[PDB]
Length: 47
Length: 36
Image (cartoon, rainbow over all chains, first blue to last red; front, side):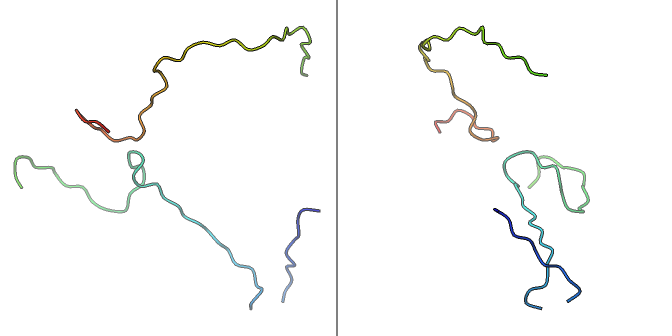
């Protein structure tokens, strides 16, 4: 049988933990998600 | 609800030339007048 289960019970080193992997691909496309930053009016012909 | 078409005629695969087609933009970056 290929699987083995966790033994959950109302019972420190073996307690369950919730794990999330939050990946990124920040270069391969136009950006679709951004942080809370405010835009400003673009200016031209000045450094 | 699938149909078995045993009427298919099986033959050795044909072949042809490929010329130079099969090239695709490796990345979503704009490049101009450059050898990459």
